[PDB]
Image 1 (cartoon, rainbow, N blue to C red):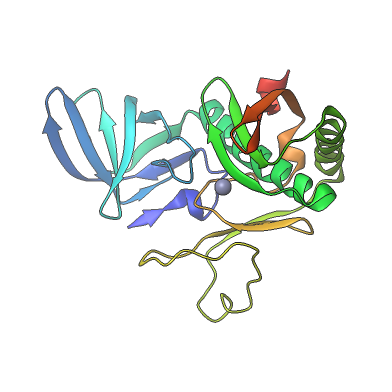
Image 2 (spheres, rainbow, N blue to C red):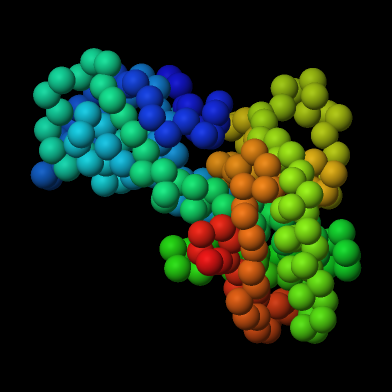
Length: 230
Ligand SMILES: [Zn+2]
């Protein structure tokens, strides 16, 4: 069945048909024929919103199937108006690409590698290998914002096994039964990622580095992108 979030990440309203209903203590876990509700992936949180005016409280994936936890019992089940909480969606889209952008700027400018990231509701972090002084950190922040306004294309795709052999990456790709998705900041960076990203760097608006500290062999950098930064 259909996962719309990987086909067009900007779809915020869609038509759906409830294929299954399971009542699990108070809540109604539903399957849909097609969904734009992201369950979560690559560190990024899942969606909330409405299915037929009934609030979606949780979205998860189990055995390749996206399940929606509804607070009330579905009545009508065909041709339903389904809408994402777009503010939540887009916030997570911006923070994730924000991380990729910074990571790509740190490597492009200074050869500095990323070894971790965290996307939280309040703040997000990225870990860069080694000590970094304030000068280099602020230069990466500047360059990130420069490429936002340069508006680079961000391609999200699942390569065919033919075109997957011509994919050049700096980190080895996972061994999986699942399909490899690629997120590519055109001209800057190309990484395997299951996230849902904006289609350009301009969509980030602005990126601000808040503060940083040492974490073992790394510099843990706190950042905000988009509406969080203002
Ligand atoms: Zn990612």
